[PDB]
Length: 72
Ligand SMILES: [Zn+2]
Ligand SMILES: [Zn+2]
Ligand SMILES: [Zn+2]
Image 1 (cartoon, rainbow, N blue to C red):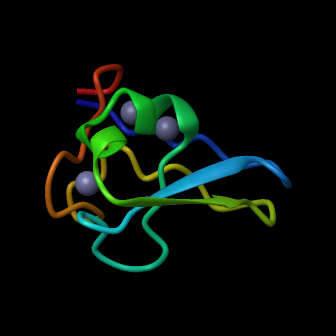
Image 2: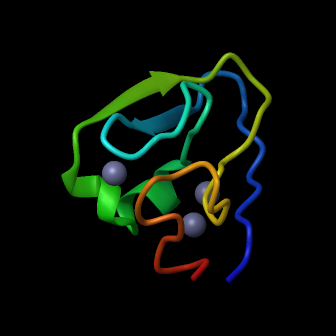
């Protein structure tokens, strides 16, 4: 697998899976979120303040489903 690493732009949607995130900072970009198991989980979309990055592909950021279809 690979890391997404997408750097969030100010104002861009970010996705936190409440069921799977290890800590509050664990986030997915829209593309990864919708290609992941988390699309059907309890989640929160928050608009980014800019900076940070998508954590898709980080096995320590997710209790389940660390990769999406693109990055696995
Ligand atoms: Zn991503
Ligand atoms: Zn991904
Ligand atoms: Zn989840």
